[PDB]
């Protein structure tokens, strides 16, 4: 979607 | 019978996406995301079909699948819910795209 919430998979 | 030909091929394809060969970019789909720990307390709102390869296999193990199309349905639903949640600029969509490629040609080689 536009944003909502992004999965915390930033550099995993 | 114990897994029809189509379903046996599913077992093999699923196994591959689960193999450490793909794990480097398949782990997002191994098991459902730890949404609560991930800070994603809105995960169950966006994801209406939370499915993962382990549950696909689980259901396959229970032989609830009749054909490989039902498998394809469930596995692709997993990649589908990923695209629902994560915007195009995210790791999990890029990993989903790549894993979609392998799975796509796996099913493409699979005769029905």
Image (tube, rainbow, N blue to C red):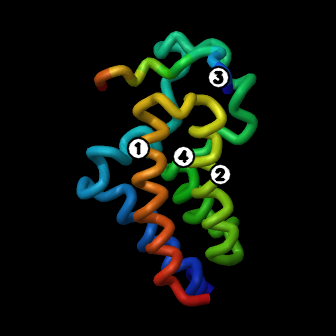
Q: Horizontal and vertical percent for residue B71? A: 62, 66
Question: Which residue is located at x 30 percent, y 58 percent?
Answer: B19
Q: Horizontal and vertical percent for residue B17? A: 39, 59
User: Between disc 2 and disc 4, whose residue precedes?
Assistant: 4
**Real-space Cα separation, disc 2 to disc 1, in angstroms:** 15 Å
Image: A8 above or below B87:
above
For the C terminus of chain B, which image quadrant?
Answer: bottom right
User: Between disc 2 and disc 1, whose residue precedes?
Assistant: 2
The answer to which of B97 and B14 lies nearer the viewer is B97
Image: B69 above or below B75:
below
Which mark is in front, 2 or 4?
2
Which mark is in front, 1 or 4?
1
Which label is found at residue B43? Answer: 3
User: Between disc 3 and disc 4, whose residue precedes?
Assistant: 3
Q: Residues within 10 Å of mark 4 (few under 14, many from 20)?
A: many
Question: Which residue is located at x 24 percent, y 57 percent?
Answer: B21
Q: Which residue is mark 2?
A: B77
Q: Mark 1, chain letter?
A: B
Q: Horizontal and vertical percent for residue B92? A: 45, 36
Which label is found at residue B95? Answer: 1
Question: Which residue is located at x 62 percent, y 75 percent?
Answer: B68
Quadrant hosting residue B28: top left
Which label is found at residue B60? Answer: none
Q: Mark 4, chain letter?
A: B
Confirm or deny contact between disc 2 and disc 4 (CB under 8 A).
no
Question: Which residue is located at x 71 percent, y 41 percent?
Answer: B49
**Real-space Cα separation, disc 3 to disc 1, in angstroms:** 19 Å
**Real-space Cα separation, disc 1 to disc 4, in angstroms:** 14 Å
Disc 4 is placed on an element classified as loop
Which label is found at residue B52? Answer: 4
User: Between disc 1 and disc 4, whose residue precedes?
Assistant: 4
């Amino acid at each position: 979607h536009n944003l909502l919430r992004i999965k915390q998979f930033l550099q995993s | 019978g114990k897994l029809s030909e189509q379903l046996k091929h599913c077992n093999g394809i699923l196994k591959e996406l689960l193999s450490k060969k793909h794990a480097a970019y398949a782990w997002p789909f191994y098991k459902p995301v730890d949404a609560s720990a991930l800070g994603l307390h809105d995960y169950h709102d966006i994801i209406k079909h939370p499915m993962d390869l382990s549950t696909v296999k689980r259901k396959m193990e229970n032989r609830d699948y009749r054909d490989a199309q039902e498998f394809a349905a469930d596995v692709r639903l997993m990649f589908s819910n990923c695209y629902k949640y994560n915007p195009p600029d995210h790791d999990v969509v890029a990993m989903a795209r790549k894993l979609q490629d392998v799975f796509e040609f796996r099913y493409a080689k699979m005769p029905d």
